[PDB]
Image 1 (cartoon, rainbow over the protein chains, first blue to last red):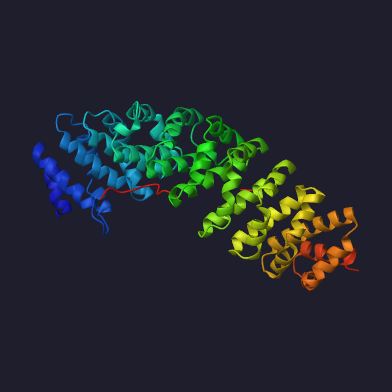
Image 2 (cartoon, chains in turn yellow, green):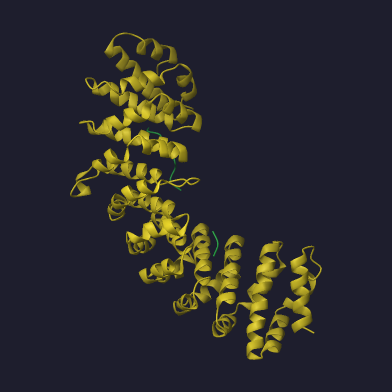
Length: 423
Length: 12
């Protein structure tokens, strides 16, 4: 449990072994659990010394200790990672990546992962120094099983961070250089490797449809669905996020998701005990019901409309908001037959009960959905029956009360409905 | 249509 001053005295000596001991003391000090002294170590000016030690090919232990210490420093605030980067650590770690000693290279992977995880700028800087080539060279083996578990996990997490963050998104050339190894890692059996790969794919699918197309062309959607059916939540969460991001794009990408068999999993996702899983699944359903009428009909065929009715009847308010969005998209883009089927599944009562809330946006969404349903009824000449139904459930009172809402669109919609169909 | 693993991690 050395002091900062003792570590400084040791590192400033002209003895390689004394420097090694002081660097190990620094590592152990920065490895503590309760408030490691990162800021005090930075103020002592020890980062350049560790960076210099990184290059002592003749003394592997000092390389390892300085790498560990710099890793733990770069794991903190953006300012501390900036200190590490300003010390010149990126090229030294990239050089260490090719060390004959495996633990040194693993520590280099770890440090570069932290630096890239800082944000977009440091990610692009790590990429510019040329880390992707040696990193992927570490994984260029016939069978990933020959590599050590921790080594592979750290490599996967570092790559996931190299795929992470937006504004700007990762350079396209780097994504193309990384994607094959990411696909090979997405087929590995270790749960942590799988979760990190799914998070990387999630990051890469968040953005314009061209990035989504990059990912989908690699043919990873079936594996993403398979993992969506996984038992480990750490795997299902990123897989569900990736599938949702994929279906936020073109109708053909959403259709590739559907062909993979994703809908079959949603009965359990829309009833999943974890609120976030339910919310993400309902949002995915909302973006699927905004697609083609063929895709709406595929939502119907899989028996997912009753599950949406259920979510609308009882769920977290945010999941209920996503469900109202899904219903309004369904009604806007659906056939008269599909809107009728939706009514027969019992949407009117829950959708009305949700008009007594205090969120103006959902009130507008619901009134728009009801306008669409009334339009379909007019198409079939059943406007009066729908009116009787919205009455018996106690909705008419809700609409006539919304007529007195501060918002203008709520006022207009409530009135319009009352006067057109209820008078 | 409309629109996590720790970024940084310490050793020990």
